[PDB]
Amino acid sequence: ELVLALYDYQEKSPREVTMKKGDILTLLNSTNKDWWKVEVNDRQGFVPAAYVKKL
Image (cartoon, rainbow, N blue to C red; front, side, top):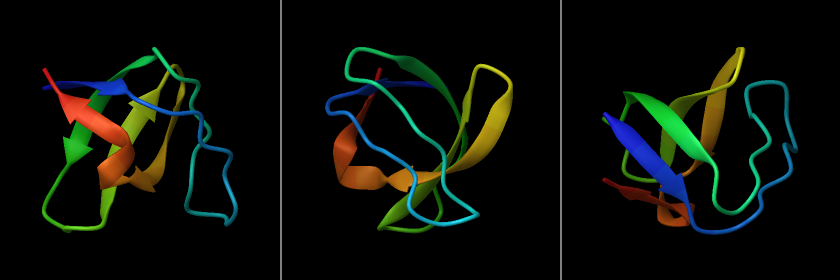
């Protein structure tokens, strides 16, 4: 599963990752309603679910 970054997001805790608007991220875990685990290049961590769109 791939998701599209709708907004920039800068990581704010150890478990988070940074993404840029337009990035295509690999979705690893979407069980939480608020925070989804993605892979952004070579890093894995959480971004807000509202800021990505499943493709």
